[PDB]
Amino acid sequence: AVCPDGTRVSHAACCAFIPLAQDLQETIFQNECGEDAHEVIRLTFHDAIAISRSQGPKAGGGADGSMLLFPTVEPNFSANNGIDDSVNNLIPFMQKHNTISAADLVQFAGAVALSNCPGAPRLEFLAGRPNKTIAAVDGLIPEPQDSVTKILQRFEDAGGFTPFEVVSLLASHSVARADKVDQTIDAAPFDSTPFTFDTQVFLEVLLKGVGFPGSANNTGEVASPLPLGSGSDTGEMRLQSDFALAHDPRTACIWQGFVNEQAFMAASFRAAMSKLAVLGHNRNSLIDCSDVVPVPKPATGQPAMFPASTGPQDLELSCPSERFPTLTTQPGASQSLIAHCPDGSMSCPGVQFNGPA
Ligand code: HEM
Ligand SMILES: *[C@@H]1O[C@H](CO)[C@@H](O[C@@H]2O[C@H](CO)[C@@H](O)[C@H](O)[C@H]2NC(C)=O)[C@H](O)[C@H]1NC(C)=O
Ligand SMILES: *[C@H]1O[C@H](CO)[C@@H](O)[C@H](O)[C@@H]1O
Ligand SMILES: [Ca+2]
Ligand SMILES: [Ca+2]
Ligand SMILES: [Sm+3]
């Protein structure tokens, strides 16, 4: 088909996603992999994972837009703490771009946001999820204090995910920060490059922790290898769950497998997101609109590196059968601050709408 703007696309049904991408980029992402992109990418996962094979359809409809359609239910569960701002940012798009369902809007917006993160894959995007569902029940969202057994079980119950797929999806923590785990600090990143979809998170979670970016006894948090912060440039935070996954016998070799393996990490993330984005649906019933997902920013191609203040002597390795790669170390005697802002500054407040969530 040829869309009103002149773009030739695979299917006429995909045309409406072109002005939706443009509006999302102009209004909330500004083509950056920043705070508002990060919040939307987390929303794609919390919308989709709230589904349970064992409990039946009444527990939740998966990638069904339930967070937007029932903004006062799930966003208020304690495991969904902080999800409200992303829901309030996307509801105005649901109302304006009103030929696209809330469910499709959530997944597409996640794809567009990810496209702004250098090294991300260009996600598959299928369209056609209905615009009516139910509110999910509580307890379906994994939490950072959860054990690996609990987490792997949640993902298997939700959609048959394998432990490989689960760790693959956690490549999203390469572009992720925390505001609620420690109430005294904002936007504590999970790796030293939270605006770049690289493999640093897999490397850095394997370093010995030496302190905390904020206070020392928050639920779901463990010691960080790069806890130094100053002004708005908050130190790195480490989640108990990511730490546990990196060291458990079921997942340790998969975790290490992504260190310094950018294209493998990106292709694996894409395959698992392909599955996540259609939870609650038969993929044979959705039409393929992958061609209207923006082309991602390319990585620079540089290998992973130990941040200054760290080195191979700091590794806490857990995979007996695979060789840890030989990496260089960024020069410098002490930790560099991790920038609060994509252009390296500290002053970049993201667009935020008020709303019902
Ligand atoms: C065991 C599974 C996971 C757990 C327990 C987990 C936990 C968390 C926690 C606690 C935060 C911090 C929220 C805050 O306090 O502000 C967070 C942030 C984030 N997570 Fe995860 N997560 C997991 C899986 C995922 C997956 C599968 C994705 C996406 C495909 C995802 C994407 C992100 C993003 C992008 C952020 C950053 C949001 C922001 O910076 O505002 N997470 N995660
Ligand atoms: C999907 O459902 C939502 C919620 O019912 C619809 O949102 C309404 O959209 C109209 C414009 O079409 C607005 O006047 C309303 O304010 C919106 N309602 C709410 C509660 O925000 C949306 O239009 C539906 N989309 C599709 C494709 O059917
Ligand atoms: C970042 O900053 C640290 C000091 O905070 C340096 O040691 C490093 O070389 C890099 O410039
Ligand atoms: Ca949902
Ligand atoms: Ca990163
Ligand atoms: Sm946030």
Image (cartoon, rainbow, N blue to C red):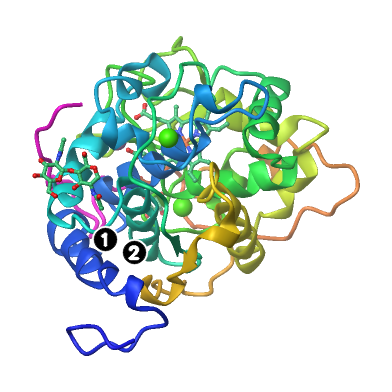
Task: Determine which of the numbered discs, if any, sits on residue 116 in the image.
Answer: 2
Q: Position of residue 71 (x, y in %)?
A: 25, 28
Left or right of residue 43, residue 20 in this image? left
Residue at x-position 45% and y-position 71%: 290
Viewer-proximal residue among 98 and 274: 98
Q: Above or below — where is 51 with respect to 125?
A: above
**Residue in view at x 52 percent, y 35 percent:** 49
Q: Quadrant of the C terminus?
A: top left
Residue under circle 1? Answer: 32
**Where residue 207 sits: x, y (%)?**
62, 37
Secondary structure found at label 2: loop
Q: Which residues are magenta?
A: 339-357
Q: Find the distance from the CA under tag 1 to the CA under tag 2.
A: 5 Å
Q: Tell me if residue 10 comes above or below residue 36 in the rendering.
A: below
- Image quadrant in which you'd find residue 4: bottom left
Mark 1: which amino acid? Glu
Q: Kindly tell me whether residue 328 is visible in this rendering.
A: no
Q: Indicate the secondary structure of the residue bearing disc 1.
A: loop
Provide residue 159's location: percent of width, then percent of height: 65, 39
| Residue 349 is a magenta residue | yes
Is mark 1 in CB contact (under 8 Å) with mark 2? yes
Q: Who is closer to the viewer here, 339 or 150?
A: 150
Nearest the camera: 236 or 67? 67
Among the two numbered marks 1 and 2 on one chain, the one whose residue lies closer to the N terminus:
1
- Image position, residue 180 (x, y; %): 33, 22
Circle 1 crowding by C-alpha within 10 Å: few under 14, some 14–19, many from 20: many
